Image (cartoon, grey):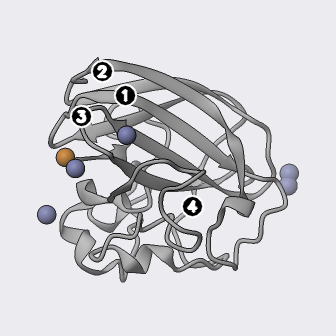
Amino acid sequence: HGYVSAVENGVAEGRVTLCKFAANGTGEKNTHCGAIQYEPQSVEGPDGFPVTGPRDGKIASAESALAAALDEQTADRWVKRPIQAGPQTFEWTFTANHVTKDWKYYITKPNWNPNQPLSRDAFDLNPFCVVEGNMVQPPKRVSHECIVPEREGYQVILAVWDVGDTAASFYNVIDVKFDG
Ligand SMILES: [Cu+2]
Ligand SMILES: [Zn+2]
Ligand SMILES: [Zn+2]
Ligand SMILES: [Zn+2]
Ligand SMILES: [Zn+2]
Ligand SMILES: [Zn+2]
């Protein structure tokens, strides 16, 4: 159980995170998130993205029954956090720091459609950042240095935390904007 955060040196909070916590240095929150608003740490679903895992249109919710609202997708629905190409630090906070296999970070394809439900066809399915977990328990907060590819405008980053001693992963999409 854990979520992408911006408490110390994280660049951008998860979509779900902003359902509960206000955005570092702007105050914005996401609204109408459903029951997951009480427990952003709980966006867990089946392993194996992208070959299996959460189906198209259910990637943002991970197929969670509490987080169905996260699968809504228009150009205006979600709070967008600024990012740039090049080095960036992503941050997870864990409420339960399970044994970890790895973390992987997907980015959307440049000319993805921001008004259709997220699918595999929306994402570059080669991750842009893979961090080894070494099948041990992380600390309660971690920072991951990643090189973010160049993009224009609104983009989504999927962060996947793959738990070493189950067949489940935690999926946090992040809404980012590469232009003001
Ligand atoms: Cu957990
Ligand atoms: Zn719960
Ligand atoms: Zn797994
Ligand atoms: Zn679990
Ligand atoms: Zn531009
Ligand atoms: Zn521009």
Q: Is mark 2 within 8 Å of ligand 3?
A: no
Q: Is residue 114 left or right of residue 61?
A: right
Image region (quadrant) for ligand 3: top left
Q: For mark 2, what is the residue?
A: 135
Give the SS element for disc 3.
loop
Q: Is residue 137 left or right of residue 179?
A: left
Any mark on residue 79, and which? none
Q: CA distance from mark 4 to mark 2?
A: 33 Å
Amino acid carrying mark 1 in the image: Lys
Lower sequence index among marks 1 and 2: 1
Is label 1 in contact with label 2 (beta carbons under 8 Å)?
yes
Lower sequence index among marks 3 and 1: 1
Q: For mark 4, what is the residue?
A: 80
Any mark on residue 101, and which? 1
Q: Residues within 10 Å of mark 3 (few under 14, many from 20)?
A: few
Q: For mark 3, what is the residue?
A: 165
Is label 3 in contact with label 1 (beta carbons under 8 Å)?
no
Give residue 58's position: percent from left, percent from top.
49, 71
Q: CA distance from mark 1 to mark 2?
A: 5 Å
Residue at the farthest top position: 134
Q: Is mark 3 within 8 Å of ligand 3?
A: no
Q: Is mark 1 within 8 Å of ligand 3?
A: yes
